[PDB]
Image 1 (tube, chains in turn brown, green):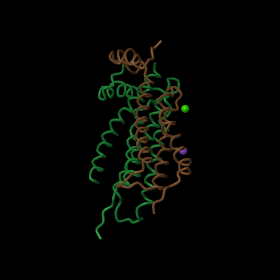
Image 2: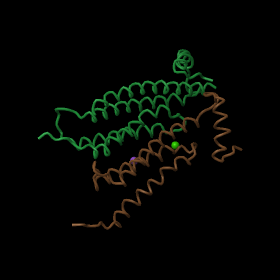
Image 3: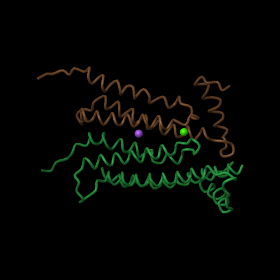
Image 4: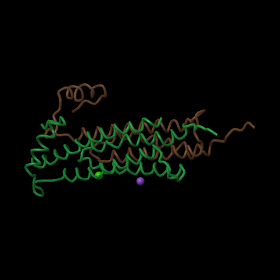
Amino acid sequence: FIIRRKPLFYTINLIIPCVLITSLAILVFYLPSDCGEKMTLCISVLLALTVFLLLISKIVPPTSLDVPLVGKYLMFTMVLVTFSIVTSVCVLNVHHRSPTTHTMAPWVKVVFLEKLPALLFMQQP
Amino acid sequence: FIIRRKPLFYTINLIIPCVLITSLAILVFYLPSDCGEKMTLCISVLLALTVFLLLISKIVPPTSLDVPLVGKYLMFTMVLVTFSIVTSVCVLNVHHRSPTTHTMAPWVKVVFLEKLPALLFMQQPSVSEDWKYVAMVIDRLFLWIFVFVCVFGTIGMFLQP
Ligand SMILES: [Ca+2]
Ligand code: NA
């Protein structure tokens, strides 16, 4: 019995929400550190991805023979979002530094204030 | 009937999310107190660990003969995260102290502003800023403690596979 699933229903109800949630995984790096909302954003994205992964596993259970590509994508994005949480913690720590508590090494200057911005087309005013 | 489980499904569905969540259990101590988001992170980690523990409880039989090693690790991590929440509350309280409202004892000076920073390799480069530095020394101290206590946690989890 060769049968071919009609994919519109699951497309609409699973793939589009998953794509929408995944698209938000990168916005934490454009959010300014002064807003005080980076952690909320990345943690919410991770929670949504985890819930979607568990639901997918309930619908189509992954197995050693084959893992759904959608589940694999969700897991990869979950790992990326955890990495983004770590990176945002580090960036927030760097942002809230003052001469009264930290001293900037000369190499930090020559790299981050001079060279790296040039590669990224930033040009500190 | 000696049967062996194929662990891929539960690996993907419980282990990887659990380790991903646990890897965030020590970040609260590297988070500046001015970001105003230590509580968010630590509370989120605690609740995520609790949810996964409850899911595991729903999977395994409700028998009291033995405890899953993964459940044991989750319980240990939740205890650690609760300790970290308490420590973060204390550090936040310390950070927001000012000369008008609090007076800093001489022993607090000689300890936190002089001795401990040397031990932790901090090297301090107005009085309100001293309170802020004390809070930064306290959570640096616990960052070392949790790393050692957590890194030795892998020993417990390295005997399961
Ligand atoms: Ca806020
Ligand atoms: Na919530």
